[PDB]
Image 1 (cartoon, rainbow, N blue to C red):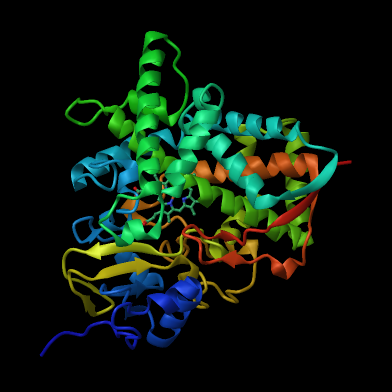
Image 2 (cartoon, rainbow, N blue to C red; image 1 turned 180 degrees about the vertical axis):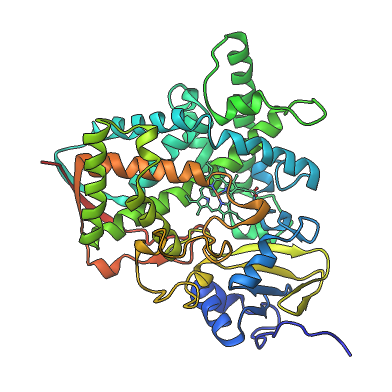
Amino acid sequence: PPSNTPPVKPGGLPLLGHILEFGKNPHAFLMALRHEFGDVAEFRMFHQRMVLLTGSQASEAFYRAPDEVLDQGPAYRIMTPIFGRGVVFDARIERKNQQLQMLMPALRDKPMRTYSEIIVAEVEAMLRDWKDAGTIDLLELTKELTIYTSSHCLLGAEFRHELNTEFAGIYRDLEMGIQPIAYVFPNLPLPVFKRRDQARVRLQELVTQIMERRARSQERSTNVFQMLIDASYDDGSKLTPHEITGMLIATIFAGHHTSSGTTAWVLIELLRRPEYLRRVRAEIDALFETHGRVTFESLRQMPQLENVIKEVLRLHPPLILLMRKVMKDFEVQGMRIEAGKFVCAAPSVTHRIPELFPNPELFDPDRYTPERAEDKDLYGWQAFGGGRHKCSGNAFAMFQIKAIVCVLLRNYEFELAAAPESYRDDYRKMVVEPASPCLIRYRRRD
Ligand code: HEM
């Protein structure tokens, strides 16, 4: 007599499964799915069967699964042309995991103090252009700021200066090549696709030249690029330009809209909540009488602003569907999920479970005080996912976001240009961010 399996939601369309109801609003869909069917709930995108894993226990089984059980490969087939064949998430488990392990130390610890200064510098620089007052699209601001700081830190000064223009064009041409038909199709050829391919080729060209020029010279800059040059596999072999190029692109895509979206939300949430705006300004102003400048050591200790970021990430996790292929029958909360099926964690859903986050719809940074529960379940809060494939860039992200917010708020008053309740997540975007017309006003402080 066969074994307990997850409940399946009624079918919808025979060609399409539930994808149309899903695509309408993905957060609503997944919220409804869990509400009706619980922690482990099956639906079907097209032919494929997805099982939504929400709550502490189901989340745990997801993040703690071996790579042999849950494969993250097929999430990113859309990206494989951008990243490169046989490059991270297109490589074989062992080679993949070494490449990821090369990134980890490039994004924490030793280079973090340099990264801080670069980020602060870049924001200071952009602010000098600014009029005494005006009206900006906040999401355009944070997207610029994040790509300038990202690229300076991950790629190096060359890409901010000499290769500024060219890289800009390359990035959008790579960006544009993220079409959903690419994921759906094994397919690759189209007009926008050769533009995507030409851009990858040009970037690898530019990476190769810079390896050689840095080597011809003796400059030893601090960026992920440099550290990937200086890295090696366990057998002593080196990364190729193909591999360095893919790994750097993956890192920039990983961090760009995620950061920029989160930064935008931190400002919006503060701007519609004066009590927290006051707490954060107080902290920032205190920093400046304590350090006199934004410093790596000062960024490490900003509890009020950390806690705001954490709560913004609870209520606005920029990645809302983390997908895996099941490669081996595995069992979650006494139900069996067969190989061939897919399985996905849903931050935006699990973050809104009352038993984990009392009064889930309320914005409350004080959830994360030592008195109150933050990590106490390490698979509740999961904006950076979890387990072996937790965000590498989470420390980088936190410093970047803190740095940007300090400098902006220290120098500039802001206010929303539209009704507070009108700023909403656009759940239709591949990386969830605030809805695109997102106007804000500014005025030099004092
Ligand atoms: C600021 C908000 C950020 C959020 C919410 C975020 C969230 C995530 C999540 C949820 C994953 C795991 C996806 C999965 O398990 O399927 C992930 C992976 C990753 N993130 Fe981020 N990220 C952010 C910023 C960044 C930044 C700034 C970088 C790099 C500069 C970065 C680099 C990465 C990398 C390399 C991975 C892959 C980890 C692996 O699979 O081993 N992230 N991120």
